[PDB]
Image (cartoon, rainbow, N blue to C red; front, side, top):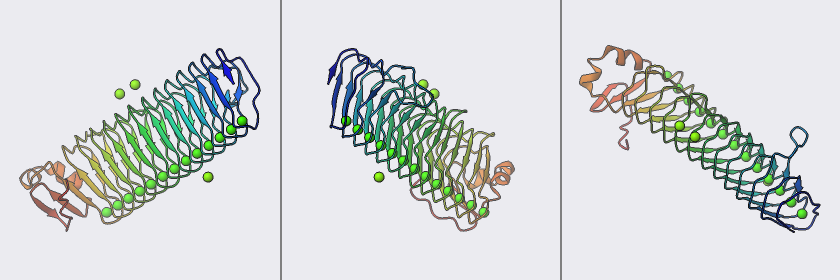
Length: 301
Ligand SMILES: [Ca+2]
Ligand SMILES: [Ca+2]
Ligand SMILES: [Ca+2]
Ligand SMILES: [Ca+2]
Ligand SMILES: [Ca+2]
Ligand SMILES: [Ca+2]
Ligand SMILES: [Ca+2]
Ligand SMILES: [Ca+2]
Ligand SMILES: [Ca+2]
Ligand SMILES: [Ca+2]
Ligand SMILES: [Ca+2]
Ligand SMILES: [Ca+2]
Ligand SMILES: [Ca+2]
Ligand SMILES: [Mg+2]
Ligand SMILES: [Mg+2]
Ligand SMILES: [Mg+2]
């Protein structure tokens, strides 16, 4: 089915191929079948009832390409769906059940739900709204900042943030054995949730990190400012701090280790505020030896 300006058409249970060279200005529903839809323009803000999809890929393993922006809701439905939107997304996107693959080249400012099963989400710009990866072992890669709330849901999820988790932003890894890497700064919040999680912050931390229950490892590579709070939760946790440590840090319950790579024994022994900040840790290693307990060597860092 070929269209320039799409203003409405009926599809069916066949495996459709829909080519739109212009904009989508009515509802588009390719229904059952493994359908392919390609739109060179925008999915427009078509008037529909609350939470109704403008573009519905339906049941089936469907494949969607949009070269422009998405301003009306997309539902990929059931099935293992593949979505590629080059532009910005300002409407809701629901990849549904199935192992879905979602690529958004621009910013995400509508709420995304990857739904059940094991989804791949890639956002070239910022995550400004809700992003729910759902159940399943999900993979989320963000090019720029998180200003909204990312919830990776149950199972063993991976998040990589290319820039900064802003003051308003959160990344909640939830249950499962999750991995987070923030390449910029953490001004908002991160929560590992239950399970044995790995959290790595390359930039500075002024916001909050919770390891949650489980035996977690947190590594911060730049300055931890005074207002920051890093709590490792119950379980047997490790905190590696590669630079200045001004903020509040807690091992909480369990057998907890801290590596202060930036401070030598000489500094530690001459800085009562630093010693008091980290005294709650069972094991404490500094740059040139051990000051408390029996920490691991941490030779990797
Ligand atoms: Ca169809
Ligand atoms: Ca379909
Ligand atoms: Ca589908
Ligand atoms: Ca789906
Ligand atoms: Ca899904
Ligand atoms: Ca999922
Ligand atoms: Ca998940
Ligand atoms: Ca999880
Ligand atoms: Ca977790
Ligand atoms: Ca945890
Ligand atoms: Ca923990
Ligand atoms: Ca602990
Ligand atoms: Ca402890
Ligand atoms: Mg499935
Ligand atoms: Mg931005
Ligand atoms: Mg920024």
